Image (tube, rainbow, N blue to C red; front, side):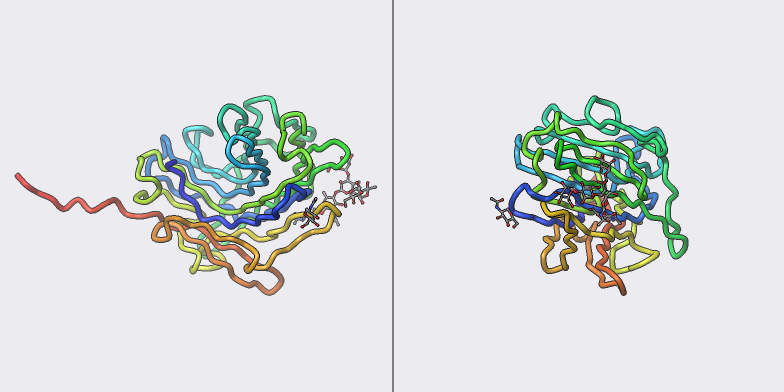
Length: 258
Ligand SMILES: *[C@@H]1O[C@H](CO)[C@@H](O[C@@H]2O[C@H](CO)[C@@H](O[C@@H]3O[C@H](CO[C@H]4O[C@H](CO)[C@@H](O)[C@H](O[C@H]5O[C@H](CO)[C@@H](O)[C@H](O)[C@@H]5O)[C@@H]4O)[C@@H](O)[C@H](O[C@H]4O[C@H](CO)[C@@H](O)[C@H](O)[C@@H]4O)[C@@H]3O)[C@H](O)[C@H]2NC(C)=O)[C@H](O)[C@H]1NC(C)=O
Ligand SMILES: *[C@@H]1O[C@H](CO)[C@@H](O)[C@H](O)[C@H]1NC(C)=O
C-alpha cells in the first residue's frame, strides 16, 4: 500500500533458481516529500507468497528519512515472512552477514547525468548448494551472504525474480498523484542516457546455467502508466529494461467557492 512500481517478473514455476544478476543504472531521482518518500531500483529474488514469502533484495535507494540524505545508496533487504515481522535494511538487524568490507553496505553511489555520464550498479547473487546461503557480489567483489538459517521457502532456490523501480508515496495518493521520480525522473521512451534501465536480466537454474529470458518470457507490471512506465529495448548485445518516470501531477483543485 502506497508503493508504486515499473518492474518485470520472471516466474520460474518452482523454487529451483540458484541465483540472478542485475546491472542497474544509477540515478538521483527527486522526491516530492523527501521526509517520508523513497525511490529505488532493485532485484527481488523470491520464493513463496503471502506469509510464506522469502525475499533477497539488493539495489539503490534514495530514502532521506532512513539514510539522512538524497544520494542513491546501495541497499539490501530480506524477508522470511512476507514483511510481517522478519527482515530489515542493510545490517540494522541480524540476517545478512558481511564477509568482505571492501564495499560498505549503504554506500552512497555516483548518480548518472541526464544526456551524459552513465553509471551502473552490477550486483550478482548465487546460492551455495552445500549450505543454502545466498552470496552477494558487487562489481565482481564478494560482499557477504543471506544465510539459509533465516529462510524457509527459499532455502533450496527461488521461484521468481523481479527487477525495476519502486517509489514509496508518504503523501497517501497510492503513487498515483506524486511527482516523486522513479528511475531518472523520465519515461522509458527517452532511452539510453535519459531514462533509467536494468540490463543483465539473468538468473541461474539448478544446473548453474545462466538463463537470459527474452521480452516474451517476462511479465511487465506498472499499475500507474501515466506516472511511471516500463519499456523493453533491444540493444546491440542484450535486452534492456527501461523504467521510471516523473510521477503524476496532483489531482486538480480548481474549486473557488466562497
Ligand atoms: C551473472 O550470473 C552468473 C551466476 O552464475 C555469474 O557467474 C558466476 O559468478 C559466480 C560468482 O562470482 C561464480 O561463482 C564462483 O564459482 C567458482 C567455481 O565454481 C565451480 O567450480 C567449483 C569447484 O572449484 C564447483 O564446486 C562448482 O560446482 C557447484 O555448483 C555447480 C553450479 O554450476 C553445480 O552444478 C555443482 O554440482 C556444484 O555444486 C562450480 O562448477 C566457485 O569456486 C566460487 O566459490 C567461492 O564463492 C562461494 C560463494 O559464492 C563460496 O561458497 C566458496 O567457498 C568460494 O569462496 C564461486 O561460487 C561462477 O563461477 C560464475 N559463473 C561463470 C560461468 O562464470 C556472472 O558473473 C553474472 N554476471 C553479472 C554481469 O552479474
Ligand atoms: C522444477 O522445474 C524444473 C525446470 O522447469 C523442471 O525441470 C523440474 O522437473 C521441476 N520439478 C521438480 C520436481 O523439481
